[PDB]
Structures are given as C-alpha cells and as structure tokens.
Amino acid sequence: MVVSIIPQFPDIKVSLALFEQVKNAKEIRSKMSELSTSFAFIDPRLVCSGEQMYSAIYKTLIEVKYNKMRTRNLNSECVLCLSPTSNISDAFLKFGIKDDSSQLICLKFHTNTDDVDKEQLRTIMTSIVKGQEIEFNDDNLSRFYDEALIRKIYKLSDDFKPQDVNGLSRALVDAIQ
Image (cartoon, rainbow, N blue to C red; front, side, top):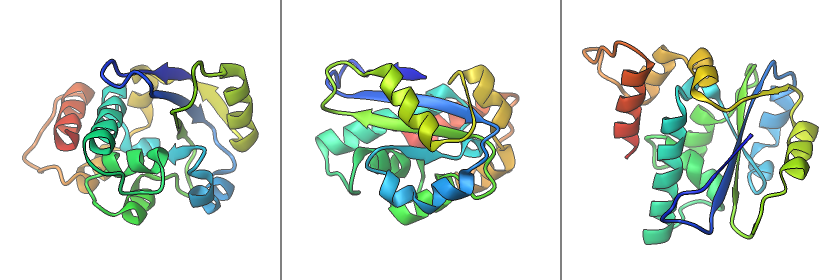
C-alpha cells in the first residue's frame, strides 16, 4: 500500500492499496455505504493511473477545505470528486466496485492519524477483501483500466485520440481538475 500526503494539506493522509483476483466483490458492494466511513472501494476499470487518483484526492481536499463537504465523509467525497457527476449515489454506481469486479482500489482518508499503523490497516483491509494485494503504481493500473468505459463515463470525444495511457491520463486529470 501507499500512504500519500499533499504538502498544502499536511494533516491529511490517504492510504491506497490495489487488490487483484478479488473473490468477494459482491459481498463488499452490498455493504459499500456502511463501509464508507472506513474505506472507499473503487473499480480500477475507471482508473488508468496514479496521477488520476492523486488529482481526485487533491480536488477533494480543495472542495472540502475551501468549500463544502457534500457527502457524509471524505472517502465518499473522494469518489464524488473522481467522477464528473454531482450526485454521490451516481458516483458510487459508476466508480464503486461492481458485483463482477476482479480488481479493486481500497482508499482511506486519515484525519486524526499522527502516524498511520500500516500493519493494522493492511490486516483490516485483507480481512475485508478476499484477493491479492499488488503494488499501487502506474504499471499495475495500466493493466486493468477500460478505455471504452472511461470514454463513455468521462464523456471523452471520439475525436480525442490519445496515443497511450499517458495521454488518456492527462485528459482525465484535465476533466477532474
């Protein structure tokens, strides 16, 4: 897993873990709203890069710090900011894990943590998720995204013709920012 801190928001830490060969996506999805106070579970088919996720996390803390929290918690707020929609139920429907998900991103905002307990967190995540943790990095995210779904959901122009994941990513960061 990765623990990420934005310089201009020094008291917030976000942990990101990536899981593959996930077996219990259905069970997790059924408890998604209840689980949101502890984790967001995001469908990697919609996420092509780390910078996409970091851009969403930044946008989240900006909206919350310099505006208003629209949802019940930061984990959910981040899913809302990752998505083009203004409605959280729509964001969960599109970006949350699906019954048929075989990979997932597990995200958690820590506000009160002075120093994240990485072994405890990993233990809890793996108690909830039945799958194999792999590194949260661009090499792995590049494997699991679905350009078609991404194009449709972020409303990318058919004219828009990226040459690689870097180009696609850059356009998503733009949509998000």
